Structure formats: C-alpha cells, structure tokens
Length: 106
Image (cartoon, rainbow, N blue to C red; front, side):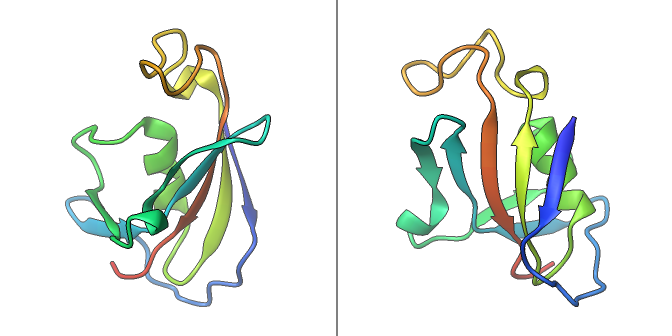
C-alpha cells in the first residue's frame, strides 16, 4: 500500500527496467514530523539497483512507478517497512515512512 502524489510534472517518458541502476535524492520523515534520513545532506546521490532486495519493497516499487525528472511523496505502511523489527535506535516499531523521491538519471 503505497500512495504516490505527483508533486513534479516529470515530462520524461523513461521508466526504470530490471537490472538497471537508478539514482534518487531521497528525504525521509516520520509521520509525526521528524526526519531520519536525507541523502542530500551528504551531497551524494543514492545509487541503488532495481531488485536484489537492497532497499525496502515500498521504496523500490515507488521508484519503479515514477519516472525521470519527476518528484513524488511515498506513503510507506509498516507492513512494507521495518514494521515490528524496526531500525535499532532510529525508527520506532510500527511506524509509517514518507519519502521525497526523485530520479536524476536512469
């Protein structure tokens, strides 16, 4: 259950495919309002490949459904997230995650 709202036009027709790299500048916040991660604070694009279960399923599905030059906010349910086995000292168990996702290339 991922809800995507198009906050950017994203006229690019390119779509991610299997076995491809994908760069996203992601910013995540907990639904109360505090953030835990921001790749842009590191000034480095987050390179991840579609598949291989490198990232949670919600983030990968959201990145797959949205395209180049597009921005969107992903509503990640705890079922598709860490859930009960939350991140140690970072994310409390049974919490939702909101991501500021955007491709730059591929």
